[PDB]
């Protein structure tokens, strides 16, 4: 049940969870879809990842207003590339509190991104330091190790069967690991497996560039990444 809304696509995944999809015509790579998440937690909405652009991200907020009609309490973005952080200014213009891995905020200017307002830090075992992620509700933020990028983070949704791998995870039939320009090829496989181990109950794996898949997305991604070493 995909819903076309302007140039974006929205798909309900669970009673309180929707996937947002936006597109950027990247010369040399076609019009690339990127997915994030929208989660209703009681009387507020939480967003995972921007769209590629400010205008698209404002359209996400317009869809939220029309389909949910509750305030967006915060957004968390999953690394410092345009598909995940390109719309930061639109969130700030809307008055939404924004969060990213401290490393993502440090990298943002050189990547052409605007930093989030708040920095997440992580324990040695990968779980977010809880004081840095206040009021995250059901969102469980995990740093699995370097993979697609050194700063990539992942998000589970407590109370659902959903976990979000962002650009770390590719679908179970993917032919490649995509853009490795900023990747850590030696650690990728272990990081993919650590994501799976952090969210063992998640049977629906959501990711940046394919429709939600089974956990075979994790095993297949890791198996491809074993070849990078
Ligand atoms: C060279 C290059 C750089 C990026 Br920054 C991308 C992205 C964004 P990402 O998915 O790596 O976060 C998507 C893509 O399709 O091709 C790219 C190629
Ligand atoms: Zn990326
Ligand atoms: Zn990506």
Image (cartoon, rainbow, N blue to C red):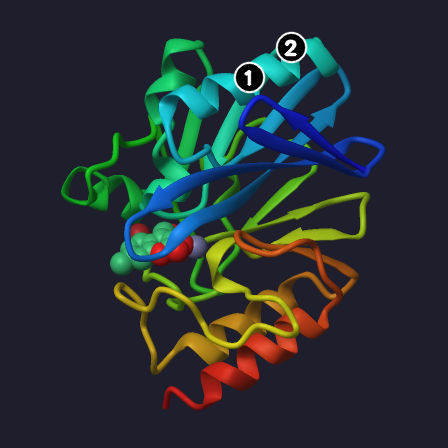
Q: Is residue 116 left or right of residue 172?
A: left
Q: Nearer the viewer, residue 95 or 134?
A: 95
Q: Is residue 155 above or below residue 169?
A: above
Q: Nearer the viewer, residue 139 or 132?
A: 139
Q: Is residue 164 left or right of residue 151?
A: right
Q: Residue at x 46, y 24 (%)?
A: 57
Ligand 1's quadrant: bottom left
Per the image, label 1 sits on a secondary structure element best described as helix
Q: Quadrant of the C terminus?
A: bottom left
Residue 167 seen in this snapshot: yes
**Mark 1, residue position:** 61
Does residue 104 appear left or right of residue 95 in this picture?
left
Relative to residue 204, is residue 131 drawn left or right? left
Label 2 neighbour load within 10 Å: few <14, some 14-19, many 20+: few
Residue 177 lies in what quarter of the image? bottom left
Q: Position of residue 52 (x, y in %)?
A: 40, 35
Tell me where residue 199 appears, x and y as whole percent. Answer: 68, 61
Residues at discs 2 and 1 in contact (Cβ within 8 Å): yes
| Quadrant in which the N terminus is drawn | top right
Position of 42 relative to 192 (above/below): above
Query: On the image, numbered disc 2 is attached to which residue?
Result: 65
């Amino acid at each position: 049940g995909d819903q076309r809304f302007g140039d974006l696509v929205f798909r309900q995944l669970a009673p309180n969870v929707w996937q947002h999809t936006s597109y950027l015509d990247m010369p040399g790579f076609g019009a690339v879809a990127s997915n994030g998440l929208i989660v209703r937690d009681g009387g507020r909405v939480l967003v995972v990842d921007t769209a590629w652009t400010d205008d698209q991200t404002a359209q996400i907020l317009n869809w939220i207003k029309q389909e949910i009609n509750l305030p967006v309490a915060l957004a968390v973005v999953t690394h410092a590339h345009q598909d995940k952080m390109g719309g930061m200014d639109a969130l700030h213009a809307a008055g939404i509190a924004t969060y990213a891995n401290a490393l993502s905020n440090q990298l943002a200017p050189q990547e052409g991104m605007v930093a989030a307002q708040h920095s997440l830090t992580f324990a040695a075992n990968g779980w977010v330091e809880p004081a840095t992620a206040p009021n995250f509700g059901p969102l469980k933020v995990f740093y699995p190790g370097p993979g697609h990028t050194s700063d990539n983070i992942t998000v589970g949704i407590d109370g659902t069967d959903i976990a979000f791998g962002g650009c770390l995870i590719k679908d179970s039939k993917a032919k490649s690991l995509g853009n490795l320009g900023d990747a850590d090829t030696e650690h990728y496989a272990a990081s993919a497996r650590a994501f799976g181990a952090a969210f063992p109950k998640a049977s629906m794996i959501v990711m940046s560039h394919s429709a939600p898949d089974s956990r075979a997305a994790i095993t297949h991604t890791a198996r491809m990444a074993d070849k990078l070493r």
